[PDB]
Image 1 (cartoon, rainbow, N blue to C red):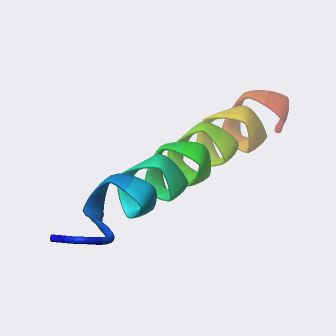
Image 2: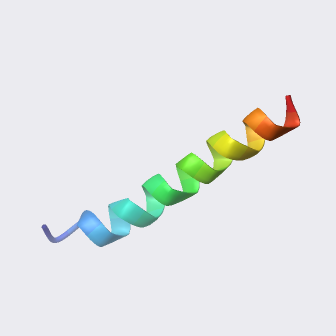
Length: 25
């Protein structure tokens, strides 16, 4: 559980990047 918050933030950034690319195409 040591890396979960740090990873959750990275996953957040990825899902937002996925959203943005979808919105641009």
